[PDB]
Image 1 (cartoon, rainbow, N blue to C red):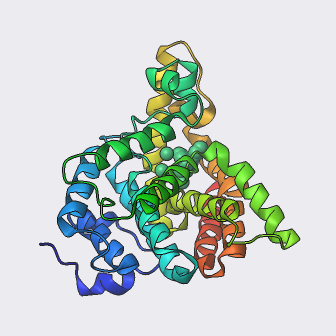
Image 2 (tube, rainbow, N blue to C red):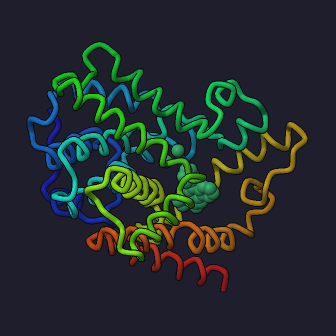
Length: 307
Ligand SMILES: CC(C)(CO)n1c(=O)[nH]c2c3cccnc3n(-c3ccccc3)c(=O)c21
Ligand SMILES: [Mg+2]
Ligand SMILES: [Zn+2]
């Protein structure tokens, strides 16, 4: 039944768009993004709406890895897609927006390292990319619910094609995998061997897009960026608190007693992770340049905080 306001129509297209002040409209914002990416008949409205509300319900009340984070990541993907639409197939356009909304499904607010170290049942189930494999499992589980399968109308080979796009995209949100991925992609771009017709290459490009979307809070306007950083640190500190209880000293980043080091930690995160990510992405997809520009702007803001 929901209809989005006229001011948003043009603003939703921009990379720096902040979903933050529209909580009641987030399910409706996602529906709009889907119709603009693959048409009004791309998914049966009833199916799609059941799927979204179920996905929403399966995001816990954690400070950062919550419903808001899912819609934020999906919106960034929507902007990338819209600015490079002809470069992606209808099946990719569909799969990626769904993968972004589901990428942190049922996150408990603990890193893969925590679950591995403390031998959590989830780490026993999934050896590497612990949470990520759980997020893809949670996505399949939601699709398997009565009248949720938005992909039922696709052909047999086209169905396993989306589920494989989704699987690969969600796994690539494992930051530990990003570093190698970005390195292989930088090699291909420089040597001039990068070929989007090659499937293994497309998988890597998609992988980087997933990282770029996952970290997009660094591409918003400084007041939004700063407020998201508080949410991520509230989540890191809670994890550190748990480690302390179990007689383990957490790394500075997860220690609330080491709050003064946050600007220095951010500067390191932007120099080692965020800037290289958007630099490589801009080389492959030149219309994604505003993401790099906004990231550089926030990097200067963190330097100013240190100074
Ligand atoms: C991007 C964000 C949220 C900016 O506030 N951020 C930050 O400040 N430090 C970090 C950060 C620091 C260390 C490891 N991962 C981080 N990720 C992260 C977490 C899970 C999955 C993928 C990436 C962030 O998004 C982030
Ligand atoms: Mg994740
Ligand atoms: Zn995420």
